[PDB]
Image (cartoon, rainbow, N blue to C red):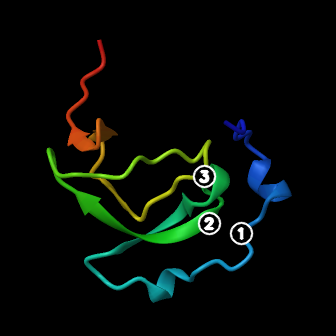
């Protein structure tokens, strides 16, 4: 679990970043998605509630391009409606 301080990616820059111009819909560009602390851009796919998902943790470097559609979270391997409190 490698703390992702505001300047982490300055020390660990994206080495082979994709361009925004390269993502093809329905996939969409995100400036900070892939790699440890999400230093790399990605063309991402969004998943619906209940759909299966792989764990996403940038703190950990586990950064699948297919992610739950915000504010859904991947819990127990399923895109889950979390409502805080």
- Numbered disc 1: secondary structure: loop
Label 3 sits on residue: 61
Residue at image point 15% right, 46% down = 49
Taking the image as shown, residue 28 lies to the left or right of residue 35, namely: left
Rendering quarter of residue 39: bottom right
Residue at image point 50% right, 80% down = 20
The answer for how far apart the CA atoms under marks 2 and 1 are is: 5 Å
Point out residue 25 in the picture as x, y percentages from the top left corner: 29, 81
Taking the image as shown, residue 34 lies to the left or right of residue 64, namely: right
- Mark 3 vs 2, N-terminal side: 2
Name the disc covering residue 14, or none: 1
The answer for how far apart the CA atoms under marks 3 and 1 are is: 13 Å
- Is label 3 in contact with label 1 (beta carbons under 8 Å)? no
- Numbered disc 3: secondary structure: loop
- Is label 2 in contact with label 1 (beta carbons under 8 Å)? yes
Q: Nearer the viewer, mark 3 or mark 1?
A: 3
Taking the image as shown, residue 22 lies to the left or right of residue 39, namely: left
Residue at image point 29% right, 36% down = 76
Point out residue 45 in the picture as x, y percentages from the top left corner: 31, 67
- Mark 3 vs 1, N-terminal side: 1
- Mark 2 vs 1, N-terminal side: 1
Q: Is residue 37 above or below residue 27?
A: above
Name the disc covering residue 40, or none: 2
Rendering quarter of residue 23: bottom left
Q: Is residue 35 above or below residue 7?
A: below
Taking the image as shown, residue 9 lies to the left or right of residue 37, namely: right
Name the disc covering residue 67, or none: none
The answer for how far apart the CA atoms under marks 3 and 2 are is: 11 Å
Rendering quarter of residue 78: top left
Residue at image point 60% right, 55% down = 38
- Numbered disc 2: secondary structure: strand
Point out residue 48 in the picture as x, y percentages from the top left corner: 17, 53
């Amino acid at each position: 679990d490698l703390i992702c301080g505001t300047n982490y990616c300055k020390d660990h820059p994206c080495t082979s970043p994709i361009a925004r111009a390269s993502c093809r819909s329905p996939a969409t560009y995100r400036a900070n998605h892939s790699g440890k602390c999400a230093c790399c851009p990605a063309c991402v796919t969004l998943l619906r509630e209940r759909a299966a998902c792989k764990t996403y943790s940038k703190e950990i470097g586990e950064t699948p391009s297919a992610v739950c559609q915000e504010p859904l979270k991947c819990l127990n391997g399923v895109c889950t409606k979390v409502t805080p409190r």
